[PDB]
Amino acid sequence: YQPTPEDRFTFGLWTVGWQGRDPFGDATRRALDPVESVRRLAELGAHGVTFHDDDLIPFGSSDSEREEHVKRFRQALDDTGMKVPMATTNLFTHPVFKDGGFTANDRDVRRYALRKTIRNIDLAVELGAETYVAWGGREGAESGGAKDVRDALDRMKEAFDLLGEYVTSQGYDIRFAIEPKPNEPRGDILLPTVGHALAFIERLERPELYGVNPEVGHEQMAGLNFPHGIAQALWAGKLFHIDLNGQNGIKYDQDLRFGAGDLRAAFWLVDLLESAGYSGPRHFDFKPPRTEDFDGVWASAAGCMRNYLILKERAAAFRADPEVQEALRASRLDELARPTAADGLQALLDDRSAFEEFDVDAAAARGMAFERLDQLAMDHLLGA
Amino acid sequence: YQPTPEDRFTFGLWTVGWQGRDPFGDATRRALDPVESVRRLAELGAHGVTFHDDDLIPFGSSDSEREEHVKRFRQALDDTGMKVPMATTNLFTHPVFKDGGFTANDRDVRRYALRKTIRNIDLAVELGAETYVAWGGREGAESGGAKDVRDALDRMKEAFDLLGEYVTSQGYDIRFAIEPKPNEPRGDILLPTVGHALAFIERLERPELYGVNPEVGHEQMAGLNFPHGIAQALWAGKLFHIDLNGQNGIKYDQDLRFGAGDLRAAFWLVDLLESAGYSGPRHFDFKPPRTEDFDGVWASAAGCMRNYLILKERAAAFRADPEVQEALRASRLDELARPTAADGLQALLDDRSAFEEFDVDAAAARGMAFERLDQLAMDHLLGA
Amino acid sequence: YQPTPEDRFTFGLWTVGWQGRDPFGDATRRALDPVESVRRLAELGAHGVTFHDDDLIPFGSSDSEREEHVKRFRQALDDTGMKVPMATTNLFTHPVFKDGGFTANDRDVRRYALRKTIRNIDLAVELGAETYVAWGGREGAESGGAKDVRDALDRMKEAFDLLGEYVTSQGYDIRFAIEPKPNEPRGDILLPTVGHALAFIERLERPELYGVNPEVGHEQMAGLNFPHGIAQALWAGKLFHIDLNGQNGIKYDQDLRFGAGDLRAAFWLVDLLESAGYSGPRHFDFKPPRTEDFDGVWASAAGCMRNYLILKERAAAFRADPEVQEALRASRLDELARPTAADGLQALLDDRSAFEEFDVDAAAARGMAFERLDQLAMDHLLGA
Amino acid sequence: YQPTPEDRFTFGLWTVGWQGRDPFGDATRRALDPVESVRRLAELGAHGVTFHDDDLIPFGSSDSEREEHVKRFRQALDDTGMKVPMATTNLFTHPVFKDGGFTANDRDVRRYALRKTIRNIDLAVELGAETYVAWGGREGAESGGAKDVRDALDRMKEAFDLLGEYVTSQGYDIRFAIEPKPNEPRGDILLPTVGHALAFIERLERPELYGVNPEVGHEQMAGLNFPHGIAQALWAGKLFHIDLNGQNGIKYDQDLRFGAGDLRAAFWLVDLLESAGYSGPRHFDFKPPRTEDFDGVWASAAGCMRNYLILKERAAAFRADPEVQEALRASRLDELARPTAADGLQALLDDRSAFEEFDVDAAAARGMAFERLDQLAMDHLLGA
Ligand SMILES: [Mg+2]
Ligand SMILES: [Mg+2]
Ligand SMILES: [Mg+2]
Ligand SMILES: [Mg+2]
Ligand SMILES: [Mg+2]
Ligand SMILES: [Mg+2]
Ligand SMILES: [Mg+2]
Ligand SMILES: [Mg+2]
């Protein structure tokens, strides 16, 4: 299970670089130089890295220091072969963003968030990023009267339309991916799930420029089925990008390494991505626990890729098993793929076997044989 | 706080008629005649009632018994003035629906579910229903291999498109409202939240025929903010109908009476509905607890309407308070309503006060004054 | 992975016998004769079965029919070699128990619940049961004013003390195990977790007669760590019995087969039970999904035992691995087992290396190496 | 609703002093001088304040600076009349505590945590604290193999027994209160709920020295009923202290001001505390949201006390209402207070009206009238 750069594993600089500061604790690790992270991840078999603007260029850098950080970073990419498929904006750390960026109540803050983003898109294009991710981590509210959500949605649509106007203006070959999260650090966050983001995209001026970037642990913080959410995103044609990690149920955002958390969900996830032919990056947005030193940081990042590779092998064996293939026919997964009424509405209305002559009790008596199928999936996951 | 039929309070027959059977217990109350429920609700000040097909016509009724139940029901509506604004299909009780209706793996079951629905739409139109609700309570899965969600979404789209073809075919003035629920009785249910339903509607052939019917307790079973969800539905123009009840957090579907459960959320809900000018029915989908006898049934249903009326008074006082109106300006809710960049993209890029000359520290230092605003909302809710 | 009756797998009659009635659906399967369940489970490799009183003797049976059901049941046990290690009372199905049994507000109901229980203890002893389980499924409330919890706890203590007086009176060699559940079918249930039950036992007159019977899915309905709960029960000496199943997070009680649900938690559970030397029954309290016919019922029950056996093999390999044994020393699990201050309070106060001369920064810099250890546990679970 | 110091409202220095640093954001407010907080809280009507050791004496202070901070603090208490009823130890911020304090795997860290605590008890006694709170925020694990929970419980018992030996040794009139929390910042925390803490106390050498300090939002992070938990703590005699705040369901620890969050639960809480005659401090452990400036800080702290006072008035009116008093008799709350079988076991066994002659159907037919009672509680909460 050794990663190849064909496996397209990518990491956020903020992931292996997380210093371990949490709500009740100070940093446990020194800061990482972006250059060293690129080198270490390259040796581990990663394909690329991603960044917030403020991960790369310390907030408040003059043009001189900005260009110096960029050229050092770019040198590290040349020396390792690492790519930068995705970039994003930090619109949540600085106190100015305490009521949001695109949907702050203060108009001048909203303008500034648009400008800060625009400046990083230019940089993202220069480094070759294909996807620009937007996570509105501060767009929301702790109390009900603080945010008119219809107005806030007007301002959110407005920001994304202006960004699409810009990329169109500049001839940029780059697409946007909205990343949902239901809560934290705001008490409730706007566009809380994959569904809410998908719905919203359909109201934008140029919907084809916009997809979603779902995260395992985020949909799981609302107790939702992450493979189900991904399947609805693929069915709609909007899965531009994906963030992999683990999460143990409904609680604070854990950002465990991938495959930790809900293991059977990771299995069904990999199975879906592999079978659907998803070809984008396998991006890990995770936090090595603050118990770890740097050796634990790199072990945890290695574990992300290893667990994807093991599950991929297990899902491929599960779908290849002839006994599984017969189990699927036994549960009528083949019939689910067939049109309900390709013959049409009128034929349906005149088909007496569809109602008048339908033997409802015989139909109800057929078992679905789902428990045998699931044990085979278990047997395959465990290698039994 | 006495209900007027202008208040448009409506009840499901299955609500006050719930016999008290639960996963671990037998019925505590005898069955109610639909006629008696119409009479009792009319005396309480209700505007109308709603029904599943099987609430009204016992499953498996000949045409003779069917027409007899309908004419008795219709007589009760004539005698009381009660209306029937909404109707829906039972596609979840009978064992034949154990793997779903529109998305059962078995094709013959899917055909039968379409036919059973079509027969009830005709009836719904005859009784004057304006909205037809679809709750796919059995569309889902307990295990991962049992349902290909992309295929299932193909079958769901197919069913809803055929239904829209039918109403179009017949010149029916009726619209569909999809009711989301994240789980129970399936381990996970397809279209689990308002967002997932909104997204899906945009893929249908005739999206303008389809809206959502959100339920308080359903979005709250995923820990989501129900007023936030409703606001996104209004912003999209899709709030055709709404189901009111209470729920205490993430657990089984409680169906408590309205205003029980999360009280502050009910307040912010009423405030939104009243201020947005929502004009549809205020529908209660609730279950009088099985501890109650029939006198408790009617007290609980009365409590539904009373609590809506109290909160409506409190929200109206909150928005009318000049001190609240000044608090809202202090938190810049007025600025949230103003366009971020009505001047346009190019003006934004050349506006040096939006980035180069923006005093980020001064902006960050302004408090939002949200806690004063929320205490005024509290003071108003409590009548202090 | 074939079960031996030394593996002590036991099943509730109500488990494989569940007819599939749920809050929104009718039965999908016919009723099972207790005799046939004993035969079928014996062929599958089960060691024994358990029962509620009403599983075995239909509610309201004359003494004549009661003794006839008992003798038929007893004949089935003689013919198969099956044992009955545990029995319990149904104090939740009948409408009379709608406000609870031991803590009903009505005094006459509380008396009747005590008598119904006492009658089943006599029967349990005759059939050789060693543990009598109490699940107060209806002890609780949907609203706050309905139950004074201090009074209710007085009545609960009173019931359990009287039951202990009885078994003492009769010279019965049998112990009680309290089964916690946080909710459903009551909105909140009294003694909601393992901790609440453990605390309560310490207030009973004869605490040594009383332990806990935790259930996987129950502690998981509050989002708690089930292995952590079991370890606190073992540490206190109170793990008399245990109920195994699966559950996918915080939602209605799923009763999935064991190993479904949170798989990594099942692994850590088995590891704890095997290493601690737990010698009681491995009892499955589960529900074959109502999608299944009887062949699926027996496949699901087989899956319960298979998954226990696979995990047991994997946990045994994990603890036997020398590389794991060195990883555990690297994370200082050996030091956690050593007394903090066997030298005593005064030595601690005068030990300058414990405060005055303690190098806090050197200590903080040691990584815990937990992520390497967890990946080895993963590698072992998956058989990589 | 103006607070009197007889109302015994107390605040943690870390509460109004929280700078607004969260997992994804930097501080929004400057640090507060403990002296200014004492002055500002005194003007607001607070009775006292509480502290961690590191709130008062910056970590790593020489004896000279330590005594200087203490004397400045003590001067502020003399000038305002403020008391210090409770103190506690910071065993979670410093990186050395990243695997816990009392249950760190490293033995030298455990010794150091005991010594750091002991030093603050001496200080707590000098300032007149009556309760010493222990919150084991870092005692736990993110992965299963990292902590043997039985060993960890041995080390936890050991630490608390040594602390009790110390206070006994020194003749100190002070008692310990254990504060449970189910998660965050560890993935799971040991002693996760009130029940788990109560159970554990019963294993300590001197249980009478130890009670619990429950927090609203903590029990609510496991979806549990906080008034139910408090009632079990009062029934056991262990409610030494209490922490008040608000929390919106199962998610990260919000620390909203009291009365925000689950409002009806705050009502039932106040009702319980007032009726049970709880005489300890009403302590607010809350965080003014980081959206606020200092004026919002003080408004939020004022809101804590106001909302307690409003609810207290409403609960007192609810219990004083003759119509409520008759409703309680109608739901048989009076019978719940009466012994089930004061007549004894043998009388119970020979009482034919308790089983043989019991009319089970008549009993089951009595409604509980809980919904009328709850609407009166609602009517009273809202002032209708
Ligand atoms: Mg995250
Ligand atoms: Mg992310
Ligand atoms: Mg419902
Ligand atoms: Mg509904
Ligand atoms: Mg269960
Ligand atoms: Mg059980
Ligand atoms: Mg807290
Ligand atoms: Mg606290």
Image (cartoon, coloured by chain):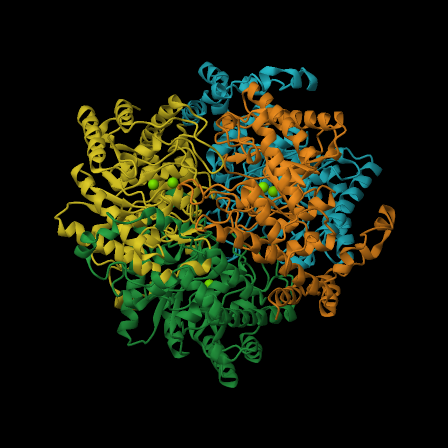
Chain colours: A orange, B cyan, C green, D yellow
Instruction: From the viewer's side, name the closer residue of D233 and D32.
Output: D32
Q: Which residue is drawn at 82% across and 40% down?
A: B165
- Whether residue B302 sits left or right of residue B125 in the image: it is left
Instruction: From the viewer's side, name the closer residue of D88 and C58.
Output: D88
Instruction: From the viewer's side, name the closer residue of A23 and B18.
Output: A23
Instruction: From the viewer's side, name the closer residue of C280 and D33.
Output: D33
Residue A166: name its quadrant. top right
- Whether residue A155 sits left or right of residue A59 in the image: it is right
Vertical arrangement, residue C350 with respect to residue D245, above or below: below
Q: Residue at x 76, y 49 (%)?
A: B155
Q: Quadrant of the C terminus of chain B?
A: top left
Res A42 seen here = yes
Q: Position of residue A65 (x, y in %)?
A: 56, 28
- Whether residue D8 sits left or right of residue B169 in the image: it is left
Q: How many marks?
A: 0
Q: Where is residue D145 in the image (x, y as percent from the top left)?
A: 45, 61
Q: Where is residue D232 in the image (x, y as percent from the top left)?
A: 31, 50
Res C258 seen here = no
- Whether residue D26 sits left or right of residue C115 in the image: it is right
Q: Position of residue D383 (x, y in %)?
A: 39, 28
Vertical arrangement, residue A379 with respect to residue B70, above or below: below
Vertical arrangement, residue D380 with respect to residue A300, above or below: above
Vertical arrangement, residue C268 with respect to residue A147, above or below: below
Specify the farthest residue to the left. D171
